[PDB]
Structures are given as C-alpha cells and as structure tokens.
Image (cartoon, rainbow over all chains, first blue to last red; front, side, top):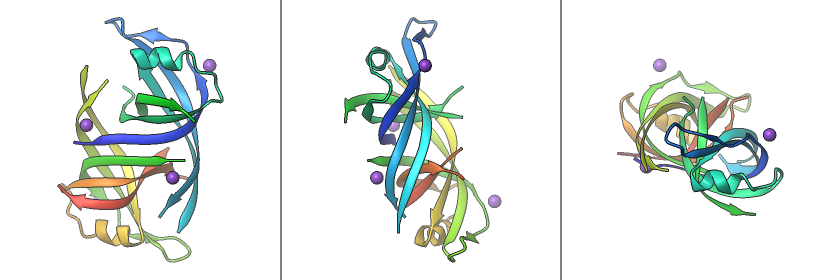
Length: 91
Length: 91
Ligand SMILES: [K+]
Ligand SMILES: [K+]
Ligand SMILES: [K+]
Ligand SMILES: [K+]
C-alpha cells in the first residue's frame, strides 16, 4: 500500500539527536509549508512534525534552520502523525 | 512548492455532506492505512482525517465505508491537518 508524501518546506527547527534502543539516530524537526494547491486555486500554509532516522538523522543534523528542503517520505503515528523523511535535497 | 500525498487506505467512516458559504459541497471522512515502509522495513499503521470538495465530495458521498481507496491529494490545516483528496480510485 502506497504511503508517500512529497513536500518542499522550510526547516523551522530541529531537536537534539537522540537514539532508539538499537542505536539508530533520530532527529525530530518541524517543517513549514507555503504554496498553492488545486481543489479553484487555494493558498495553503501549515507546519508539520517530521524526523530523520539513520543517515537521514545525520543529514538533518547538519542543516541550518531556515533552509528550504525538497522532501520525500511517508506518514506514521508519532507513538498525532509525523512525516518520516526518507529522501532529502536542497531548494 | 510541491505538497502531494499518495495513500492507499480504507474508508473508515464519513460525515454527512456540508457546504461552504459559496455552496461548494464537502464530505469529511476518516481513512485507515496499513502497510510497510522503508526506513529496515517498518510496519506502519495509522488513521488520518480527510475530505473531498466539489465533485470529490459527491464521489466520497457514494462510497461505502470499508472500501479501499487509492488517493492522491495535498495536506492542509483543518482550520491539526487534514488530507484533501483531489483524485480517487478503487483498490
Ligand atoms: K509503502
Ligand atoms: K531547536
Ligand atoms: K503545490
Ligand atoms: K458516519
């Protein structure tokens, strides 16, 4: 079953790196989206919690807040929903 | 800025049709997702609020709860986040 989110958003802030019991690094962060959709065009603005695990945690850990990111990933239950980023690029 | 969600999920329930002041029909509903992702494979399960506007409201309004839907759309602020379905198919 497909569960794929593509989102170009601004990194607002990120938490300090933490780890799962297995030692997998995780960086929780907040993304901000601003743009338009098609439903009559509609301006859309919202923020969404996200996180990077493993290599993605390392990647997010070096990105300066305010950077615009082109993200791809999947949605999941926090433990509320959180955006799991599996792919990332600038601009 | 891209904001696109692709989700194959089961329609759990839907509210009665309502309208915006302009007369645009809207059907709010709840979707349930079950499947796997790639982060090491990870089982993922969650429910998410959604809605269809205009023709999409009419389409959802005739779909029986329990039906599996292949959805495409965008995320937005409820007024919390809600999945705006702009495209829909069965299976
Ligand atoms: K999947
Ligand atoms: K911070
Ligand atoms: K867009
Ligand atoms: K109902």
